[PDB]
Image 1 (cartoon, protein in one colour):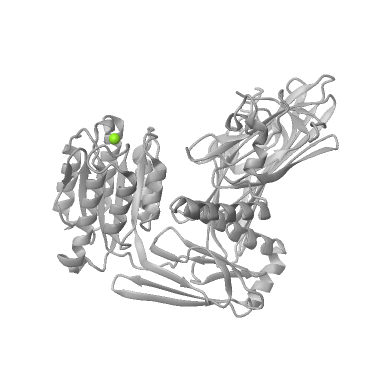
Image 2 (spheres, rainbow, N blue to C red):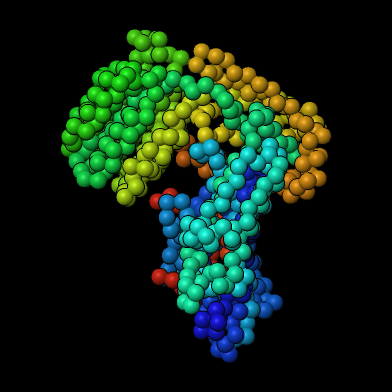
Length: 600
Ligand SMILES: [Mg+2]
């Protein structure tokens, strides 16, 4: 029998509906306690940090419980006088680089049937020429009816679709994973029988341990992907068949003593590989910063065979230099790229990129964090993006995120691990091939009530620009978009008009779910944008952005950093409600059913 201590997992189902990159997850688990005693049951799964929980329901023999979303402050008032912290008590916590762990332990009645259902949503982001859907599969028992169903609907059409299950042998995956796509519709169905779940023909344990990955991309022949539905729009921009731009890239590398060991080795290895794949038309230099600041050439040099080999030799040879002069290192790298303005104007049409890697905070020279931010942004002056890589967890990552945000870039975390070299290569490949610069998506001011970031410094091959917004009443029919940008010595310009007939056709094919997901796509991107914006503004404007993010989280019912989801009707030993939160970037209690709470 599958059951353990009288408890068996009758069914465990993951249902993912993807509509124009908006991914709607529903995970449903039904556990049955056949024992005549009380038994403890678990609902335990991993979800991506990028997603927002939107609903949670528990039904025990008709007794229904639902997560009520509210201001986080209100939800955590029960923790103030309590012996446990909300972080320790919460059902959700960080469990890895990109995933969070949702865990609840519940004492169920005898002869009981309990159904758990968790809903979470995200907008899939394109990277490396694909979208990726990752589902952590790990039932701590065999499941009678296990299913993963992914239903994809893309107006532009699906160009490719794949489904990989690492934990399954190639022969088992073939018979068990059903996938197909035609036109706008794609489907993946994974329905392993109990026999197919056992690791061995006559062993009790289940091989369903690992990750179920679904990847796809949409046809990009049609340069215009403007999707309008019920006063909300989503605009996807990723032109194909563009010529790679030549680029000027400077690497600013921390060589402080703390880098000693694996970090410097993995950093050097990544630089060697990056230099090895550089294209002849690019220009580059290298900057090292410890206590002293050091540049390989002091100016942008061409990526010739000799220069690349000399740079690789310089990478292999350098040694560490104690402290960390981050201000000097960045300003030096910026000075080199800015030579293109006066000394080297023949490189001015290239796309410029500045990448910085550090494992610690500034200890030499300018150490006032606010001053460094000022120094950097005043030197770059919006000419090129800055990509900060935080190596390990001794860096002030918020400091790195703000700096990149203030300079048309983003920050990325590098985890100290056996694959740090691949992480660095992985990130660089996202910015390695600029195709357009100064992308300006323009929409008629008379029609737009709200909109997301519409200016983007660089567009890279393999990635994508997405804009969403809300349309004013009676302006949807004539809605349009103009996209301007520059290539290397070229001007880019297109116009996208709503295809009214096509929208109605799409609405018929996908149903009213299309309207809802486009709006919720806008809400998701707007909330994320508010969370990003709030971190780089003064405390007064930060409160204003927070209130916008709070109100939108409540309106659309998202569990975000400003909201929590509480479950009335359950209590731990101290009478505390289950609480669900969004953990931040920086002892397992068990619950019982309790219908009473002290009256106010
Ligand atoms: Mg350091």
